[PDB]
Amino acid sequence: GPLGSSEQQVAQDTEEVFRSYVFYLHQQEQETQGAAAPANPEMDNLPLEPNSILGQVGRQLALIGDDINRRYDTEFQNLLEQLQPTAGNAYELFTKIASSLFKSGISWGRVVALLGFGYRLALYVYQRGLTGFLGQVTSFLADIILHHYIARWIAQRGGWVAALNFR
Image 1 (spheres, rainbow, N blue to C red):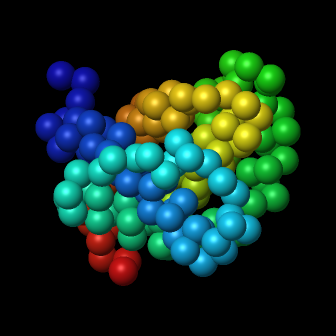
Image 2 (image 1 turned 135 degrees about the vertical axis):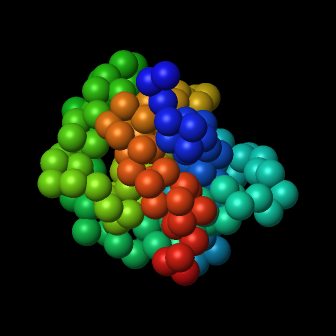
């Protein structure tokens, strides 16, 4: 009905891709920066599937995002200043970022930036003392990717596994 068969699969896969992205980006920061990396035990305790395709997509997008998302740091941090103490407007901020990132179209680099904002939002919410929010951030991201036709765009390119071609 409203969803394509592959579009629907892509939208259902987003949660695992983002959880993997988060785990591997956080682990990469620890491996390179050690104790200087921003701590977040919730991101250390992410159990992943054993070496799944979506897991390897998340890992590769994290390796890429560590590089190409540095250009968005100031924009992301400036927007996070608007986060309410309860994090009640977290979804609204996430949709503001998506609107800005995809204003001129969709690309893999823009998708990676969106995942990167999700990571920074989850990290900051935790640093402000709110625990157990990673699941909500993940749902927010999956919601944005489906409704903004990002899942459709990814499906047209072969699904999340297509991201493996930027190793």
